[PDB]
Amino acid sequence: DIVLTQSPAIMSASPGEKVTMTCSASSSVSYIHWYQQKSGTSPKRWIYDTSRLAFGVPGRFSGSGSGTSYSLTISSMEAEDAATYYCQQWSSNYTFGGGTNLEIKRADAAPTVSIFPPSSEQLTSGGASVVCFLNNFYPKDINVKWKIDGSERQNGVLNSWTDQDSKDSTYSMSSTLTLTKDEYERHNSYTCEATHKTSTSPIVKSFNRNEC
Amino acid sequence: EVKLVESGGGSVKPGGSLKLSCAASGFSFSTYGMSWVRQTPEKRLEWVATISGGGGYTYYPDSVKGRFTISRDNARNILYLQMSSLRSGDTAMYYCARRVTTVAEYYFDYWGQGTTLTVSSPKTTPPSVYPLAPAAASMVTLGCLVKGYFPEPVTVTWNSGSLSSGVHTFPAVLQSDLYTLSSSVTVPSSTWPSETVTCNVAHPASSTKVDKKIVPR
Image (cartoon, chains in turn green, yellow):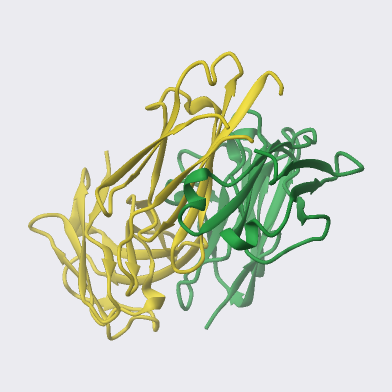
């Protein structure tokens, strides 16, 4: 019974800027330590005790805090740093923080939208999935609405999100609407549309069923 | 180099028992305390056990105390985590970590690669693969919807590795206690459909690999 809540859960920095994420405790604590975790690999040692850096970590990292509120600071941001940073205490119960997702920030990108009618193979099985790919955009926060025959739906939409690209530093999203065969053939014009802080009006992509 | 390499795990029905092991290399095992730490799919870090350098002392959190036992054998440089009466909350990837002494505390220096432990009662199901071809420009985005599979690690390889540099893979989202993922690829119009694009789905938990030539409607 000793919680750590780490303050900015997701954070986006551009290269060359300062970065301060915080770890705040439910009660007073002697020291706190930090680990780093990139996609697909375990946590690595980063900062131990409070201000002591591990052999590998660059010198532009820094640690501080006393009592209830400690904090890891990055002097100048470089793209090699993006990973989730956990804190951990060692005084009572060995508790980890929730982490701080560190993101690279780039110029905004609007997605490259692609819609796909269900396969001739799935339909013969009793089902029909309509799928929409919004590809290479930034930032990440998007809204997507599927409109069928001009009305709209939210039942059975599955939405998945990549991790930030290691080259262009974008994100990709899939959107799958899982109907029935009979539900699918009940309508004509399936449309997915993407709203975003880039374009003012949505990016629409459409097809009609009674066509094939 | 310091190595920590852990073995065992997979899919167990709730109530089963299991044992995880971890093997040590390139450091004197007996002189260090060794712990396990678990991470939830939602990237949640929870400490689960600790043994001393000798036998000496063991310590446990109050989420597994009673079900887990942590053991070393310093003849072989290997940890052991026996887990009895597994429940649904025990699903996680489990790492072994070295614990080193600091000024007044301790700290986890090296962590292994983890094994994964899925506690659940459903069958292992192979995946249904459906092609995603369009029903008009100079670059084509194709896809493969990979749907209805249980044990979660799947693999999608496109033209047998060739098109990696233009592939987006989308994490499997769960619903209906089956997993559903998607994968997209991008291709210059000069490449398709003049040449075959085929995505390839392999599902090691069932030893099933399916192929799908994306052909154009």
